[PDB]
Image (cartoon, rainbow over all chains, first blue to last red; front, side):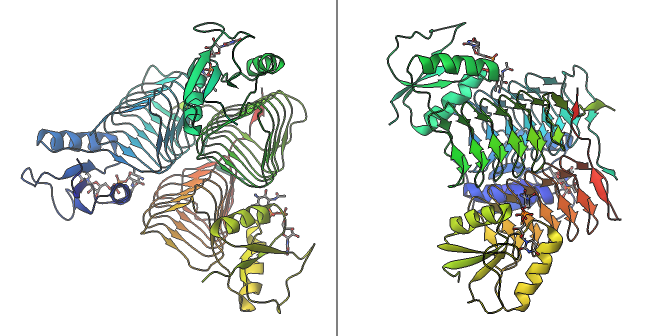
Length: 194
Length: 194
Length: 194
Ligand SMILES: CC(=O)N[C@H]1[C@@H](OP(=O)(O)OP(=O)(O)OC[C@H]2O[C@@H](n3ccc(=O)[nH]c3=O)[C@H](O)[C@@H]2O)O[C@H](C)[C@@H](N)[C@@H]1O
Ligand SMILES: CC(=O)N[C@H]1[C@@H](OP(=O)(O)OP(=O)(O)OC[C@H]2O[C@@H](n3ccc(=O)[nH]c3=O)[C@H](O)[C@@H]2O)O[C@H](C)[C@@H](N)[C@@H]1O
Ligand SMILES: CC(=O)N[C@H]1[C@@H](OP(=O)(O)OP(=O)(O)OC[C@H]2O[C@@H](n3ccc(=O)[nH]c3=O)[C@H](O)[C@@H]2O)O[C@H](C)[C@@H](N)[C@@H]1O
C-alpha cells in the first residue's frame, strides 16, 4: 500500500506536474531529489515510494534502473481523471505517469517508465513500449505499436494498425501514416509566416 | 427503458470499445453478433437493445438498416464523461456512439449512426450528418456542417463555418480551411523521415 | 460573491457557450446584451456580474474596457470540468473563459480577457498574455509564452519553451516550432484534395 511520502526524482518542470498527480492520488508529502540542485538521492534513504520525474526517456531509464537496483519501489502516478478500460493493462509499480484526461481504451498495454502526458489518447489494442513518452495531446489510433524509448511530440498522431520502431521520434504536430521498421525522426511541416 | 442485455453487432476492435461504453451505461451483459465469427444475427432473436459496432460507415449503415427493418431498437451508447450542452440535439435511439471525453456544445446536432470517437469535439451549432465518423481527437469548430457518411481522421479538424460534402474523407491530421461542395479525399502532409 | 444573474455581452455563438458555462457555475439567469440586436448595454444597468462573450480579441478588449470603466465586475466563467493546478494562477474577476475539459498545469499563468476554448491545454509554467484566444483543442507545451492578443487556431500547438509575439495568429492545425520575436500570421498546410 502507498506510503504517506513520495520521493520525486527530478526537481524541474516535469517534477512539478508529477507532484500534482501525486497530491491528487493522496500523497501527503513530496520530497524532491535531483543530481544538480537541492537534496540528492542516496542509497541509504528510507523506503518511501519513488517516482522518476524526468522527461528525457534515456535519462529517466538510467535513473529508473539505479533506483530499482537500490531496492526502492517506483510507483505509477495516475491522475484520477484518467479513464482506463477494465481490459487495459498498465504495468504495476513501474514508474508510469498518466496525466489528466488521458484515455486508455480496451486491451491497450502500457509498459514500464512510460509517460502518457496531458489529454493523450491510447486507443484499443495499442502497445506502448517501455520508457516511451506520448506528449500532450498526442494520440495513437487503434492497434498501434509504439516501440521502446519513442517520443511522440505535442499533438502528433499515429494512424490505426501502425508500428513505430524503437528509439524513434515523431515530431510535434506530425501524422504517422505508414509503418516505420527503422528508427528515425519523423517530422511534420512547421508553421510558416505568411 | 434500457434492457439488461445488449446485442453488439461487430465483434472486433470497435466492438470492444462499444462494450466498455455499454458497461459504463449500466448494461449487465453484452452479446456479440458478427457475420464472420461467433454468434450470428437472426431475425428471430429476443428484443434486446442493439448497437452496431462497425467503424466502416457504409457497412454500419447497411447493418443498421437490416436491424431496424427487423423491428429491433438501436440505442445510443453515450459515455458518462461526454459533456453535452442542454441545447444540443442527439437523435434518440439512433445507434450513435459517443466516446469518453467528447464535448458537444450549444445547439450542435448529431444525426443517426454517427460515431463521435474518443475526445472528439463538436462545437456550438455544428451539424453532424448521419453515419459520419469523427475519429479520435478530431474537432469541428463553431457552425461546421459535416455531410452524411463522412470520415474525419484522427486529430483532423475543420475551421469555423465550413461545410464538408457528403461521402468525403478528411485524412488523419488534416486541417480543412475551405468549404468543399464536391466530395473528395482531403489529406494533410504525412510525417517525413529527416 | 456571485450574483444570481449575469449579463452576457455578445448574443451569438460565443454567447451560447458562455451561457452554458455560466449555468454550469450556478448562475440562475443570463441576460444577453448586444450592440446589433436585442437588449443594449446601458451605463445605468443594475450591477450584475458581467461577461464579454465576443470571440474577436480586439473587440472583446474594447468592450471589456467600457464595462470596467462603468464600474461593473467582469467575472471569470470557468467550467467545473476544467482542471487547474493549485499552483496555477488565473487572474481573478478578469473576464477569462475556461471551457470544458481544459487543463492548466503547475505554475501556468492566465492573464485577463483570455479564452481557453474547449479541451485546450496550457502546460506547466506557461504564460498566456491578456486577451489571447487559445481555440478548441489548441495546446501549449511546457514553459510557453503567448503574447497579448494572440489567436491560436483549432488544433494548433506550440512546442516547449517557445515565445509567440504579441498580436500574432497561429493558424488552425499549425505547429509553432521556433520563437517568433516579430508578430505575424503563422500557418500550417491546409488539407488538399487527392
Ligand atoms: C525545459 C524543458 O524543456 N522541460 C521539459 C522536460 O521537463 P524536465 O523537468 O524533464 O526537464 P528539465 O527542465 O531539463 O529538468 C530535468 C531535471 O532532471 C534533473 N536531472 C537530469 C539528469 C540527471 O542525470 N539527473 C537529474 O536529476 C535535472 O537537474 C533537472 O532538474 O520534459 C517534460 C516532459 C516537458 N513537459 C518539459 O517542457
Ligand atoms: C482493424 C481496424 O482498422 N479497425 C478499426 C475499425 O474497427 P472495426 O472493429 O470496425 O474493424 P474490423 O477490425 O475490420 O472489424 C469489423 C468487424 O465487423 C464485422 N462485420 C463486417 C462486415 C459485415 O458485413 N458484417 C460484420 O459482422 C467483421 O466480421 C469484423 O469482426 O474501426 C474503428 C472505428 C477503429 N478504431 C479500428 O481501429
Ligand atoms: C460566426 C463565427 O465565426 N463565430 C465565432 C465567434 O463567435 P462570436 O459569437 O464572437 O462571433 P459572431 O457570430 O460574429 O458574433 C459576435 C457578436 O458580438 C456582437 N458585437 C460585435 C461587435 C460589437 O462592437 N458589439 C457587439 O455586441 C455582434 O452583434 C454579434 O452578435 O468566435 C467564437 C470564439 C467561435 N467559436 C465562433 O465560431
